[PDB]
Image (cartoon, rainbow, N blue to C red):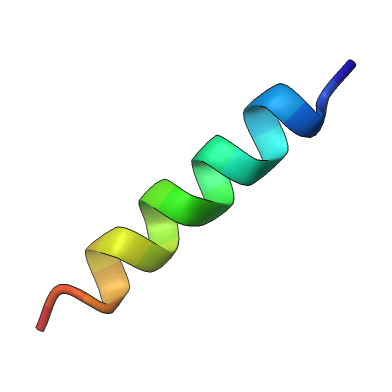
Length: 20
C-alpha cells in the first residue's frame, strides 16, 4: 500500500528543499 506514495513524495519533497 501507501509506502509507494509516501517514500516517493518524501524523497521528491526532500529533493526539492535539499535542492538549494
